[PDB]
Amino acid sequence: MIVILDNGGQYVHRIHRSLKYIGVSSKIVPNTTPLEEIESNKEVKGIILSGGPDIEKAKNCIDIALNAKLPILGICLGHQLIALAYGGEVGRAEAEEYALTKVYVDKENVLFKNVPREFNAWASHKDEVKKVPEGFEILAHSDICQVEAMLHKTKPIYGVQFHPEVAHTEYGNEILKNFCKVCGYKFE
Image: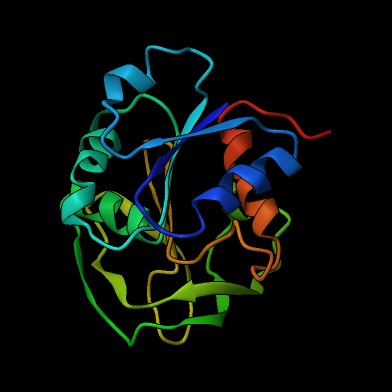
């Protein structure tokens, strides 16, 4: 199963339901849950750091991003938290508003397998990754966001600025499916 850290955003339940829909179990836990309690249960195959409003009140995600021995997906705030954790930079970009963003996939990566190189994703751009951490690379961009997605070149850590877990993201479930594949699931 996948543990979802609830960073307080309103789509946390859409993560659980989207995963269940492709036949993966998941559990929403408070974002203050210690990494050591998550990793005590060998049933936990991966961690998703959800979207939420305040990075200061998701400080515990920094420890999980740095020190977890399981695959991680950061969604919006989770993406930004991964960035900060590894000494990248994060800041205000555009106005607050959810919009369909045309996203370009810039390289061949496991996270976007069976996703067209061009797809519409549901995203806010209140905040964005400004400098990608050392030893990470950009997987995707839009006209307004240089870092729509990134991965750790040597750990199984993935960041998306957008929300794959809402139906408004084309191939959103596919992107979740792909992360689950890194976490040991097969979808034959």
